[PDB]
Amino acid sequence: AGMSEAPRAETFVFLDLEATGLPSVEPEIAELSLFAVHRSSLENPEHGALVLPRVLDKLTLCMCPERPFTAKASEITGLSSEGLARCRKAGFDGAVVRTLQAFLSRQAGPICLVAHNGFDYDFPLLCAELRRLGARLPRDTVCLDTLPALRGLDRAHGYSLGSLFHRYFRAEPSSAEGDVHTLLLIFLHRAAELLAWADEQARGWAHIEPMYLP
Amino acid sequence: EAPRAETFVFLDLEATGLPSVEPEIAELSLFAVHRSSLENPEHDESGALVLPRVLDKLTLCMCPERPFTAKASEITGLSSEGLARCRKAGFDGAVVRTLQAFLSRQAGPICLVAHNGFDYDFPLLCAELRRLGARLPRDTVCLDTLPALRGLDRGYSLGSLFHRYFRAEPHSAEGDVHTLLLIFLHRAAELLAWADEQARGWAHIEPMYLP
C-alpha cells in the first residue's frame, strides 16, 4: 500500500570500482565491473549450491587515472599507473561513456544500480567521473546500497564483503570483477529481502551527488 | 612492414547449432589483452600462470530468433525460454554499439582470437554484424588457435588442450574464453609468432549465411 516514488527496477546492475584512494584524495576509477541481471533471476536463484544466474551481462574496463595511486590502493588492487599505461588504457573518457551506455541500453529498464557502500563511495565516485564528461545514465535508474540495506534488514530481524560472505557461505571468497562476483552471491542469498528493500527504498540516481567536481 | 597487432581480443560464442542449421549467437564473450601481457606471462606467488591483471571484458546474452538445437541447449546451459524471460533482445544495434565502443577502448591494430574461428566464430560473428551494416576497425586481423596449435604441433577441443597443458579444468562464453586465454598464455611466443606471420585480415572473412 506503501509504494515508493522510486520506479520498480527490471534489471539490477551490480557494480564495483577499484580506485586510487579515499575521498580526501579525489580518487579516480582504475577499474570498473558491471554484472547486469534481470529481476527474473533474482526472483529464482539458481543452484545444491547457490550459483550466478546463467543469463548475465558483464562489463569490466580498466583505465589509466590522471593522478597517482596511493601506495595502499595499488597494493590492495594490484593496479598501478605503469601497468595501465603499459597496456595503453586511456583514462575515463568518451569511449568509456559510450561502452557504459551501450551496455546499459542492452538491459530491460528501469535499472537499479547495486554497489556495496555505494552511497558513500562507488556512486558519488561514478557520478564524479561521468559529470566531468556530462554523461547521463538512463532516466529513472535507481540506487541500492546493500550495506545500509543489509544492516537495516538485520536490525529488523560485520558487514564487509568478506564477513558477509563467510557468514552466509561458511567461508572463502574469490579485483573489480571478483568483488562484484561476491556481492552478487551475497545478494542472491537475501534476494527476496533485497528486492523488496530496493523497491521501497532505492534512491534516484538523480539524487546522487558527485564525489567532487573537475 | 605493416604494424603488428597491439591488442589481442579473445572471444567465444555460444550459438544454437552447427553451421547447417544457420545458428545464431546466444551469448558472446570478449577478453581484450594488450600485447605486452602476452609477451610477458604473469605468475602466481606459487608460480602458477594467471590471467593478466589488466583486462577488459564484455559478455552479452541474446535471444536467437530461431530455436536451439537440443545438444546446443544442453552443453551451453542456455535456452530460448531463459533468454526471453530475461528480456535479452537479439543481435541488434545495442549489441553493435556496445562492441564498437568496447573495442574503441583497445590499442589497435586488434587481432581477434577464437578457437575454431575460421570455420565458425568469425564467419558467424561476421554474418550477424553484416546484417546491420556494422564493420570492425579495418586493420583488424584474425587468429584461429585450432589450426595454429595443430600447426605448431605437426585431441584439440579446448577441454583436452587444457588437460594436456595444466592438468584439470575450470559451456559458458566467458568460461571458454578464460580457458582459451590460459591456453594461449601457455604457448604465447609460438602463437604470437604464428599471429604475426599468418593472422588473416577481418575483411576477408565471409558471413556464414545471409538471414
Image (cartoon, coloured by chain):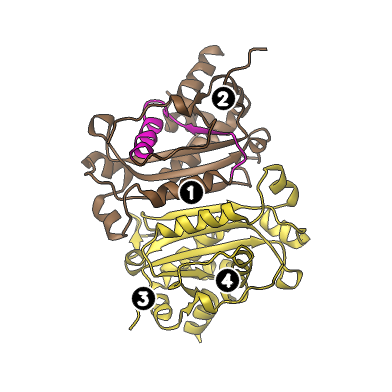
Chain colours: A brown, B yellow
Q: Is residue A110 magenta?
A: yes
* Label 2: few (<14), some (14–19) or many (≥20) C-alpha neighbours in 10 Å: many
- Residue A151 pos. (x, y %): 48, 19
- Is residue A172 something that shows in the picture? no
Q: Are marks 4 and 2 in contact (CB under 8 Å)?
A: no
Question: Looking at numbered disc 3 in the image, what kind of residue is underneath it?
Answer: Arg
Cα gap from disc 4 to disc 1, whole angstroms: 22 Å
Instruction: Tell me which chain the residue with mark 3 is part of.
Output: B
Which one is nearer the viewer's eye here, B152 or A10? A10
Q: Which residues are magenta?
A: A107-132
- Is residue B103 something that shows in the picture? yes
Cα gap from disc 2 to disc 3, whole angstroms: 49 Å
Q: Quadrant of residue B156?
A: bottom right
Q: Are marks 3 and 1 in contact (CB under 8 Å)?
A: no
Residue drawn at the location 49% of the way across and 74% of the way down: B142
User: SS class of the residue under badge 4?
Assistant: helix
User: SS class of the residue under badge 3?
Assistant: loop
Instruction: Tell me which chain the residue with mark 2 is part of.
Output: A
Q: Residue tagged by mark 3? A: B4
Reply above or below: B6 against B200: above
Apparent side of residue A197 relative to residue A65 in the rendered image (left or right): right
Q: Residue tagged by mark 1? A: A59
Question: Looking at numbered disc 1 in the image, what kind of residue is underneath it?
Answer: Leu
Dot label at residue B122: 4
Q: Residue tagged by mark 2? A: A198
Cα gap from disc 3 to disc 1, whole angstroms: 27 Å
